[PDB]
Length: 249
Ligand SMILES: CCCC[C@H](N)C(O)(O)CNC1CC1
Ligand SMILES: [Co+2]
Ligand SMILES: [Co+2]
Image (tube, rainbow, N blue to C red; front, side, top):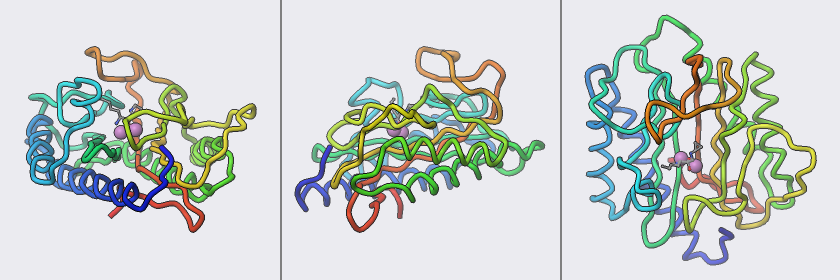
């Protein structure tokens, strides 16, 4: 959506804070021995506490408050009896709505220590990709400058991007214009960012695979070569004075 009122801005900040709080709380509780459903239950209780509603459930009838994706799973993992183990690469993606406004945020991290430093590496680079992407965000700038930054960041670190997963406009729903925020540069795109535009920027950085496929169920996205993939997502408002991240505390 395009923000036009201070009341809209406040509503977006409110739901962004809630999603960030939930994301942080879940991440802190992610340790060997907890199940992903147990992690999802935390979101259930906090959403209730803060008067928010799961976007996955509301918008997509997703069977879970949040999406928790582990190891082979890159996105849209279904919270379940799956137990977290030492070294797991975990992505927690929290999206919700309150009073008609939405936020969408996500983080990939490593549980304890893995025997392969690549798991942390994709997390480090996804974080850098996001930072590099938002440095480009201002009214009048090309949307493609986001993907350009993400892919350049990946190349600088001998890594790849997931080409078939993207960001998206957000605010009054989980998906609105721009339809797609790519992780790479499309030279034919003339789409510009404008004042008040609200975007979900979610770079996916991969150890090898350049795309995801259907996973173990109708929701989860995976890679058949079990690449390690990290995502960092925030909800961002494009303003003249710089980007406002509703989902950063
Ligand atoms: C169940 C829907 C979750 C949607 C999710 N919160 C998203 O908007 O970041 C997009 N994810 C797809 C890019 C993998
Ligand atoms: Co998300
Ligand atoms: Co999103």
